[PDB]
Image (cartoon, rainbow, N blue to C red):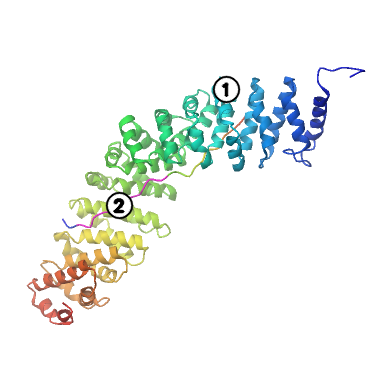
Amino acid sequence: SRIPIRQPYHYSQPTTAPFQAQAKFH
Amino acid sequence: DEASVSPIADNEREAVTLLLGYLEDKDQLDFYSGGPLKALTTLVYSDNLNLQRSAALAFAEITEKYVRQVSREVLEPILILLQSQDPQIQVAACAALGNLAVNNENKLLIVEMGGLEPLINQMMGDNVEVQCNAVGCITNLATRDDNKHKIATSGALIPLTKLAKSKHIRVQRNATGALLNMTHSEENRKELVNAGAVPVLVSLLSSTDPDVQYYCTTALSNIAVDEANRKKLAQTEPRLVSKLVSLMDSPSSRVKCQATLALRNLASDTSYQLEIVRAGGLPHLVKLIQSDSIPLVLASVACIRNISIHPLNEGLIVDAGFLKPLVRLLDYKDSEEIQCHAVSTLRNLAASSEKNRKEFFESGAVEKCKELALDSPVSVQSEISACFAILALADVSKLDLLEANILDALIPMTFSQNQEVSGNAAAALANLCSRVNNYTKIIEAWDRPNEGIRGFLIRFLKSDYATFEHIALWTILQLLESHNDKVEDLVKNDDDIINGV
């Protein structure tokens, strides 16, 4: 019952993908 | 004039002949300045439709050729061509504006000169080519952080949402690309959600087009970053989880990766921690952590790290055969992040229940952990430390751990200057000494290795960390109440008792 507790922010936190779209024209 | 007359004014004939002169020596002369520019300007202002068209085609081909930073005066005429009603002029002018919008400064300059409303009204006309090109302009302009705010608060998200549903693939690609580029900041994401473009994206996860489905996957992945968004999506579109899960086996690999990451972002919350497992994503992930491609491995192990947080999933996760691929991932030395994710996963699995413990041990997890308990980054050391601290609380497992020479790993870790490592290692060591039927391995490790338990107690008695002093004392009392003569006279050394202050 006295297990070590995981920190509330101890997980793989979400990130914004760095990809940016490029336009294609005529 | 006096000898003859033409339908075209003389300044414009001037412009056309000069332009003819320039278009066949592009090499030598700069076109965004001087002669070429005044020619093109004159042709933009003209009465004659054909000359205007000629100017537009010129601009388009030039901007297609090379992109540089340009002045006010390069932009105004193109902005006036944008005001035209001639379809092909609109096409060429837009294409030129986008080719210019490739360069970063030109993005800000274009938006600041008010190109947004022209582009928007172009997008709401129903000529497909000008839709494609104008939307394309918005796409390229939406790649500068300064702009996306102003783009969002201009009302362009409505025609973008509209055109993202186009039956024409070029338009759809540029549109979803734009919508994707509107998901790099939190408030842009808020604005994007408000426009009601989320159901469109979620639906377009089923697109057969590589570019479209990748853009929508990345966009949704970016939206899942915000918690409020996650909740609202869990409420609004329930099908998302399923579709992403199926996208983990897409033809294109970047889609598999990005979808896995989206599933991680979602797995930040518990409802998704369960619903991903219901959707049967465990197989895909098992396949993925054993893969060659390290971005897939990274995505998948981060994802499973997040999913393993919820206790109720544990059994399923073990019964899907995750343990040994994870232990295998512990051998990966070159990626600290993969190690951290895998060991953290192991920690989660162990911390959840005390039921499939046997399978956990049989996976060879503890021996690998012992192996890396000193030769690893402080992150991995910390997670291994927590893991040991967890395992050493199972009374039935205590003697087995002691027998596997776990003290040879624990005792040195209590020297680590990291609070987590030293602390949890010392706690584990302490709980291994508590109420076991056999104090053999405890005895053998009294002095060896690394000064042994005696050294440990002596040191931690003089720590200022109250908790550490207390785990030392408590250890001592647990050894005194062991009912084992040998150890009780091992305590006869009073380095311990005059330092027991």
Residue B15 to residue B459: above or below = above
| Residue B228 x, y percent position in the rendering | 33, 38
Residue indicated by mark 1: B128
The kind of residue on which mark 1 rests is Val
Residue drawn at (67%, 32%), measured in percent from left and top? B76
Q: What residue is disc 2 on?
A: B345
Q: Residue furthest left?
A: B483
Residue type at mark 2: give it. Answer: Thr
In the drawing, does residue B69 fall left or right of residue B494?
right
SS type, badge 2: helix
B403 or B117: which is nearer to us?
B117
Closer to the camera: disc 1 or disc 2?
1
Q: Position of residue B346 (x, y in %)?
A: 28, 54
Subunit of label 2: B
Quarter of the picture containing the N terminus of chain B is top right
Q: Residue at x 53, y 38 (%)?
A: B147
For the question of whether residue B274 can be seen, the reply is yes
Q: Where does the image place residue B437, in percent across and percent down from the top left?
A: 10, 67
Subunit under mark 1: B
In the displayed structure, B482 sits above or below B196; it is below
Q: Compare residues B254 and B356 and report the one nearer the observer.
A: B254
Rendered image quadrant of residue B250: top left
* Residue B80: quadrant of the picture: top right
Can residue B405 be spotted in the picture? no
Q: Where is residue B280 shown, x and y percent of the image?
A: 30, 38
In magenta, the rendered stretch is A3-15
